[PDB]
Length: 133
Image (cartoon, rainbow, N blue to C red; front, side, top):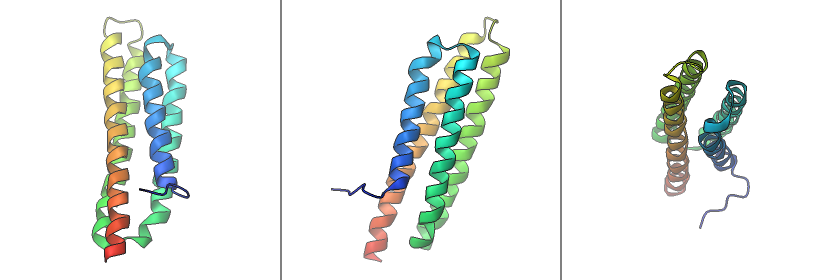
């Protein structure tokens, strides 16, 4: 089917989605310090992802290029939101509202992982239409 051999966009989407699933399982049992770290890795994998998307762009149909650049900005918003919720989680670590901002962290990072997965499909789609065009 698909050859992922030198496919960094693929690699970084997977690394990111993995990092999100890690947070999802660990958020329950991590002190405030412990999730700061996992979100920081989510940040890093994302900037790697965005990076490898940038290097790939020039080589696609303009239509796709424009759309993908759009989802890049969206991915960053998703990260901005995740960090927001992590801050809430932190200042509410001893309040009855602790549990809810852990739920919103999981939501935020879940929508980020999904948007990354959606981008992989868009990129894969674009690579194919490039072959056709």
